Image (cartoon, rainbow, N blue to C red; front, side, top):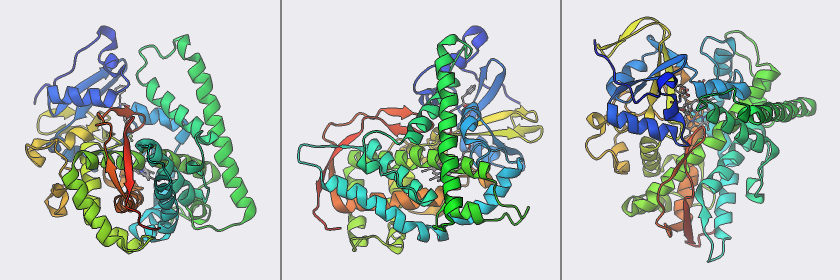
Length: 454
Ligand code: HEM
Ligand SMILES: O=C(COc1ccc(OC(F)(F)F)cc1)N[C@@H](Cc1ccccc1)C(=O)O
């Protein structure tokens, strides 16, 4: 049995001031580089252990030994995402019920149904870029977030956010972004009761009311009309859990909708942003990806079958998820006393944090070149060890949106590479903003149209 290292302390605040930074995940990554595969992290009233090696993470991913934990980030997001799938405990009735009802909505087979809606928004992105003047550039995370919010609005509840028509966000989205900001800033506060945060707390309750009022009105307007659009909302109003035989109640459906809107706004847009970043920084890779896009997407409207043929585009997306998994951590608790790694005794209830960006840099798995962007690592899916690559979390609590996200990202990146050449005209220095997720702030490019009709 071994004693684990611990980063520098601040007296009675223990390690908590290490999170007083706009880039706490990047700070924890640097601490893992200094300390190794495991370190203890303490705050007043709390202890966790940060894991970075595939050796320890493969054990943490054993569902017989560990279940999903709500990290302080997720407990704070739970104040507006409720017992939706992302912020429920595995043992809460609504977790398994919603999981069983929603799984078929999110299958690879269901993607054939969403494809046409995804294409609608992707074509809006391509037309936006085709219509820029010579002197203009693209704001990449801004445009990718317009796309992914619109896609989940249309697939989620047949609602057009029309993000490509506006500068200012939808009222729901201003409240959702401000609530995500509160939840993520609050876990850093050395003195959460400071009157300096009274206004933040007032605003947070206001933002919860806005999200609830607006989503509850979407649900009630849909129940009033009777309309049967092929969207997640229809599936949730109609679907029955085989186990309980019950449908979701209207409060839980509201939490699921809020949850899908957080996911679409925060995650897939980060992935696309990082992927285009690595492509403009790696022109050999961009050429191989653009060759596949040109050869496969032979029609002005991509088909479902064509998007499945974009093998290398998919490899690019996986390599971007390796280096910068946009949802960069997940948390576990020990179901019972257990020894991790033959070395670290844990008691029932003990928490672990999985630092996904560090897992994905384990040289014992990936080799010495871990910082290089090389989609060829993913040529042969067989060759990636179990629990080596975990950008969608683990087991029954893995991302239900994984197929949706990869379908949208493969479609959109393929269309981008078909329709334009890209220039890193500013020699962009990567600057990773942390919200719920990671995104490359201030990333801009110029696109030169290949002048291929839609
Ligand atoms: C590249 C895009 C995305 C990434 C990287 C991502 C990542 C993740 C990860 C890491 C988790 C596990 C969290 C944990 O263990 O605490 C998760 C859970 C989840 N994700 Fe995603 N996600 C993505 C896109 C989406 C989309 C598009 C949806 C839905 C519209 C979605 C819905 C969910 C839900 C509902 C859960 C909770 C599942 C459950 O516990 O039953 N995600 N995601
Ligand atoms: O380590 C992290 C990283 O933050 C994120 C956790 C989840 C997360 O959600 C997602 F990965 F899904 F995006 C995003 C960021 N969070 C920890 C930070 C912490 C706070 C107080 C005491 C000890 C540790 C946590 O939220 O518990």
